[PDB]
Image (tube, rainbow, N blue to C red; front, side, top):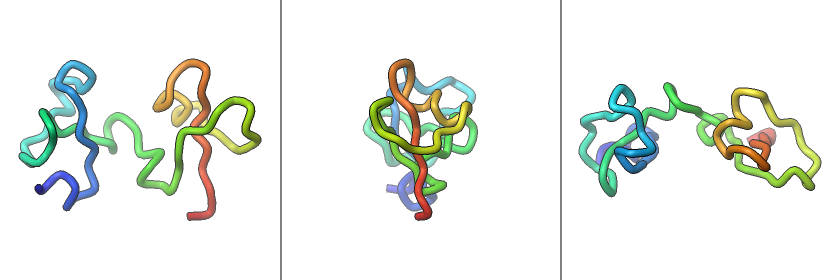
Length: 75
């Protein structure tokens, strides 16, 4: 697997835009570019519920979606 070797995220070709679809050959179906979509994970962040107190960015909140907020820690 090469995607994981570069720190990419595997996604369905339906979720992943034809522009983000990489050729790293190492995902369930297609490799998605986290640098083009979102790097909430790469920056040491994770999806958190709206009931959880944390600092979420407007561009990172998109990652999780509606009804969720991408929180980040000092990691």
